[PDB]
Amino acid sequence: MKNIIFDFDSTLIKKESLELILEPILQKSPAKLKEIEYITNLGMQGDISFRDSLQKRLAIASPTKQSIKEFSNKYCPNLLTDGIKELVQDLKNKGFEIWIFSGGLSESIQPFADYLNIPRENIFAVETIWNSDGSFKELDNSNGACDSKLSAFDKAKGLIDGEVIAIGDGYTDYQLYEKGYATKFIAYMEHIEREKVINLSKYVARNVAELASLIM
Ligand SMILES: [Mg+2]
Image 1: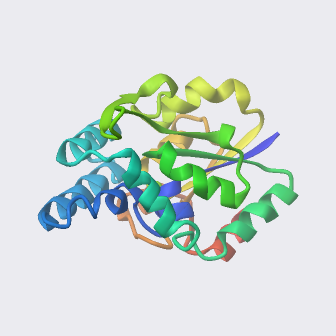
Image 2: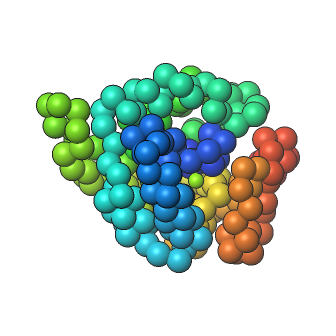
């Protein structure tokens, strides 16, 4: 009967996952990676829709099955926010159910969720279909995550009872509160300072101690 919803990118992990997944693919095209970063920020500032952000980034470069595995191999667990595993366990100990709603790729999140002891069934993120050669075939938006966290929450809300605290660095996290799906939004700005989102938020944390201080 109480719930924490984390974003993954720049919240549970220190960086943006899709950019890191694509960086090897784009070593010869550094401007494309800067472009992907810029588009990510437009979506996370609420300047363009999340769907438009995701589609444009995938148009710039689409990942492969193996690119996600290489990302996991390199960055799980060292890319995790300082102190996050212990915070997650402290929250579980205090009775919170932990969820991840993200615009990152679900397959990239799973190893991290495993490490953090967050159930796999509690991850509502961007699902991908690969061709038999590992290349990108298409998104699978059955869960709504390719449109927004709002759509994903709407589809999943029968599984979520009671208070919901949304924690994240982006406008899409704020939207969960705006729409009333979350009872509280805490802007998480350890890794990035998003002025538009900070300005909308009543609560801001810049490390896991500050975050704990706002919740427990
Ligand atoms: Mg984020």
